Image (cartoon, rainbow, N blue to C red; front, side, top):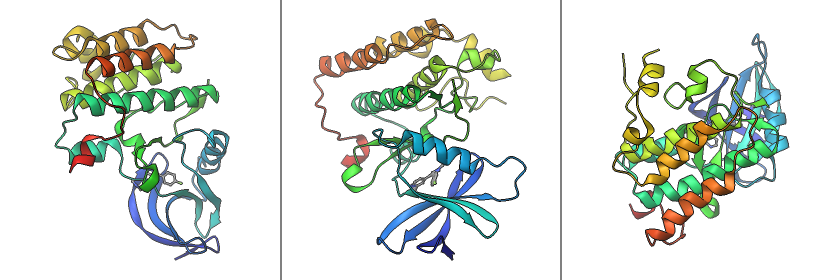
Length: 265
Ligand SMILES: CNCc1cc(-c2cn(C)nc2-c2ccc(F)cc2)ccn1
């Protein structure tokens, strides 16, 4: 199917917040792309608002390039460069187990992605593994951050901060606290409040950070304690948090070579 004079629409990949994702080809450039579709007539149009956020974020490391934006038939269309699998897909492919080196390589980039979004006056509000994608080819070592559908100028229950479960307005600290649960999720293979059948808020609040992080380097606990200590309007010390993991990376004797667990398959 023809899209905006130069794109050929392929099949559905998955779904984002407020729209389905499809494979595509940029016919003029000879490159595969990813296409997000939104019904023109939806009660709450958001595709064009999100495109403006991506546009403002352009130039930042690990911010995907948006190639075209417009309307075609029954849909609002956004075209993005093709990226690789999400960290959730890669975690599942690695049998839900990442080495400490992989977790630390990912933490370094992920803290930087969040800091960049915050430097652009936005909070993401949905920090989770499926919102981080690895690049392809020459950009294969790069962690990209996606989905600005829930973003706000200053989510998922499993990774929500305690302040979020309390019903408090999300701020910079909440994006970082979510990353801290994402990091522990990669370390454990699961979180203690996962698969409960409300109950998540109670389980999170009754699980001390020292119990959550037991058997893992103290840095994961120190990271979460720092995020929980941040005030609503506080500018987080991103450099301190990256240095916490960097010092542990050096103590372990690891090389910053971008060779992740999946690269060894
Ligand atoms: C997973 N690799 C294919 C892939 C998927 C995506 C992708 C995923 N999700 C949940 N959303 C998007 C997306 C695609 C286009 C767009 F305009 C806005 C967002 C992106 C690139 N490459």
